Image: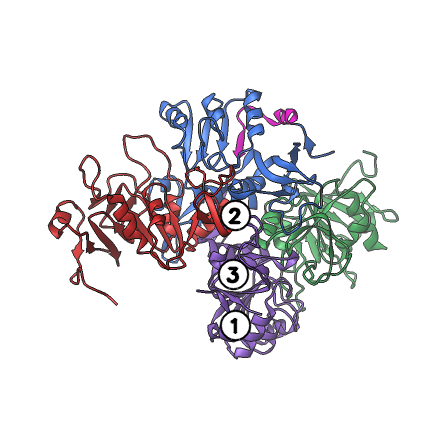
Chain colours: A blue, B red, C green, D purple
């Protein structure tokens, strides 16, 4: 068929209990329309994976504020008092992972690797429940891959094949979650023709992109 | 002005051409006290090199704190995997971070205080294990008067045995081969005050306050 | 003509929109038998998607064999880490590779011949371990007449338990839930011929040669 | 201060017994002048790391032909009979690693990771001498990072800060070895001024590039 679809169609991909990766650092790089659409769907019991919870009115915040998320996996939640409130309250589960570890877990999930050794978190609470290996006289935490049912991606430019480019600091997690999810939805700022994006400028090849939201 | 003297001293530690990471809070001030002839490149965790002040605000350009920033000529963008590949891979010559506690074993705690809401560690852990030089910029004592430079951190660690340099408005400490050394004392202060305001065990440099080549 | 029937049959297996990897040798012929309406994207190990025939030769544009090739509109370049992240991460819908030996345990050998000088495995291991569908396109028997579809590979393995589909000019085999199944026989061939020329133990589909 | 340096001065980095990573796939992406300078220096007992040994007159071939290498780590050597003969004879040690594994080893070396789990090579001769881990009921080979004393890189464009872009299939290993070596030397096809390379077009940031070869 085609990868091009309206936002209204995206609601078809949402379901209860599903795990979703969302791009963006502090809301910068988050697909707004997809998130608003995810909120409009009314789906609950979500497990969201992202770098952070952004602010209350940005990023994955609105989803958390309106109580549609049961679990969060991220590296920072400080700028969203609601996340913390719900974490403390018990309404929502939160897993705080070192950023460099989290992104590598996502990449591993995406790159078909069974795990990786990192020195980050050794001797801390991060070590709890994890395997530790000694190599080269140094202790490493063995971190395991992360995957998801769905990925919500924002891109700058996007052609009809799904080749993506990104703008400034809006890139962050997006290129990695694109490989780590079963199905991928991209929300490009600009839709271009195939050939308009030079081969040496494309960051995320269209092969990993399943569906494209049109302008 | 304490924060400014700290920032000023840390700025003098950086070498020309260094790749530097400045944590949110006090360390960001270090960029405002770089000596003449010292040029550094600032790395931003959210994925770019060549961080700088705002010129014209851009929605897709912010710092690790999510606040609008800018870039200098020759800046480079990259994703988070690359970012922490750089950070963890030892391509950051120096990171300057704040601190809640530091101890004689060079352990660090600066991402959570027991009793207060947990904000998360972010990229602090990767930064302190990965950076070639870990500089901690911190006030000597807390606002309640409690010690922050201890024998052993009581708060949850960011990392263990990671700190190389501790800079306060009262003194400069260095961790060399496991041992903690008091290498500088601030003007208007003496060794006894630092000792009194410090629970950590440390040896004092014999050649304290002397010129070097 | 054998190589061509194999290639054509393998070509008939590919789906519209599939990301495909074609190894050097026989598999590239698959590119010449794609049915109408079927469009695929070829991945090159050296790091790009949208591989195609030469248009105007460029020194910095070659295939996995280092020979000059071309690209199609919408092609994307990337480094080797990304390339084998794609390959190993299961982002290749299908790989078509040649073979020296295959066995009932779906093991593969296709990167070295004992007695001949060793060339190296290249990206074959990642490809057969990573691909969503692993298609082996090879002649049934060697040039000496000996079987190549065996009970157990004698040559150094490329991978173990990796083959999903084996396409020969005499038959098509499929590995389903651990067991090896003979699903198609080529025209001009008989079951006794396939059995005789195959040392591997396999079960035959009851509804052989029927419409779906 | 400048990163610009002549080819003659660059030879000062070459020495016997040194381990060197060299970019290029089948010679495509290899810095020719740097290899010629390395050959001209007369250094021996080298350990070369590259995707392959290319052909006799390209890539790291000339270094192998002139017996300047004692050890090779690569994934393919078929197009260079000299590599094979010196391998068989015993004059040269050769480590054949799966391509996807090799590049990940280099990436680990560059990214400060202690190792990774891969399914590639399980049940083969590649498994020999390596640790195997069982996770999710699946067996993985534990592969460890690779680093080098020096990296010889080719780029298409390069500014005075060392920001690099690459052209077509000449990229391959170059971006990864740039992070995995103590010292890095780049040979750009074109030297531009800072600002001519857009932030979202730069593949290798100048931070990891130490010296630039002037034409």
Subunit bearing disc 3 = D
When the figure is inspected, residue C52 is found, relative to residue C15, above or below; the finding is: below
Which residue matches tag 1?
D6
Q: Are marks 2 and 3 in contact (CB under 8 Å)?
A: no
Give the residue pinned by disc 2.
B78
Q: Nearer the viewer, mark 1 or mark 2?
A: 1
Circle 1 SS class: loop
Q: Quadrant of residue C211?
A: top right
Most foreground residue, C209 or C22: C22
Give above or below for A210 relative to B84: above
Mark 1 vs mark 3: in front: 3
Q: Is residue A13 magenta?
A: yes
Disc 1 residue crowd, few under 14, some 14–19, many 20+, Cα 10 Å: few
Residue C89 coordinates in the image, percent (x, y): 59, 45
**Farthest residue toward the left?**
B192
The answer to whether any part of residue C183 appears in the image is no
Q: Is residue B134 above or below residue C59?
A: above
Task: Find the magenta span and give its range.
Answer: A7-22
For the residues tagged 2 and 3, is the chain the same?
no
Residue that badge 3 annotates: D160
In the depicted view, which residue is nearer to us: C54 or A54?
Answer: A54
Residue at the far right: name it. Answer: C188
In terms of depth relative to the viewer, which is nearer, C121 or C212?
C121
For image coordinates 52% across by 79% down, the residue present is D42
* Residue B55 visible in the shown view: yes
| Image side of residue D196 versus residue A132, left or right | right
Residue B2 placement (x, y as % from top left): 24, 44
């Amino acid at each position: 068929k085609t990868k091009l679809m309206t936002l209204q169609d995206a609601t078809g991909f949402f379901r209860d209990g599903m795990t979703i990766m969302v791009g963006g650092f502090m809301g910068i790089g988050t697909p707004s329309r997809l998130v608003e659409a995810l909120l409009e769907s009314g789906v609950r019991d979500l497990t969201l994976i992202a770098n952070d919870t952004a602010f209350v009115d940005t990023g994955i915040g609105p989803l958390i504020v309106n109580g549609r998320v049961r679990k969060v996996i991220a590296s920072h939640i400080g700028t969203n008092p609601e996340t913390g409130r719900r974490m403390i309250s018990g309404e929502m589960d939160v897993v705080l992972v070192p950023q460099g570890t989290l992104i590598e877990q996502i990449r591993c999930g995406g790159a078909g690797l069974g795990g990786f050794l990192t020195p980050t978190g050794v001797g801390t609470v991060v070590e709890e429940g994890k395997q530790t290996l000694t190599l080269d006289g140094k202790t490493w935490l063995l971190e395991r891959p992360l995957r998801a049912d769905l990925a919500l991606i924002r891109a700058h430019r996007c052609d009809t094949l799904g080749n993506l480019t990104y703008q400034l600091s809006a890139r962050n997690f997006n290129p990695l979650i694109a490989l780590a999810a079963d199905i991928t939805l991209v929300e490009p700022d600009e839709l271009v023709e195939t050939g308009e994006l030079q081969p040496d400028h494309i960051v995320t090849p269209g092969a990993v992109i399943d569906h494209i939201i049109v302008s | 002005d304490a924060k400014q003297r700290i920032a000023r001293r840390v700025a003098q530690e950086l070498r020309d051409g260094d790749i530097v990471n400045l944590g949110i809070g006090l360390p960001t001030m270090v960029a405002n006290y770089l000596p003449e002839g010292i040029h550094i490149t600032l790395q931003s965790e959210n994925g770019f090199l060549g961080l700088g002040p705002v010129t014209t605000a851009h929605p897709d350009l912010v710092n690790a704190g999510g606040q609008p920033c800018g870039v200098l000529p020759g800046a480079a963008m990259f994703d988070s995997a690359m970012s922490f590949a750089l950070i963890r891979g030892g391509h950051i010559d120096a990171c300057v971070l704040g601190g809640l506690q530091v101890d004689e074993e060079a352990n660090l705690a600066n991402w959570v205080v027991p009793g207060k809401m947990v904000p998360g560690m972010g990229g602090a852990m990767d930064l302190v294990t990965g950076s070639r030089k870990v500089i901690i910029a911190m006030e000597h004592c807390a606002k309640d008067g409690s010690a922050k430079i201890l024998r052993r951190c009581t708060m949850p660690l960011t990392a263990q045995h990671a700190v190389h340099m501790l800079v306060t408005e009262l003194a400069v400490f260095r961790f060399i081969d496991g041992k903690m050394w008091l290498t500088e004392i601030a003007d208007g202060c003496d060794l006894a005050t630092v000792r009194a305001k410090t629970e950590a065990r440390f040896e004092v440099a014999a050649d304290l306050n002397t010129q070097r080549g």
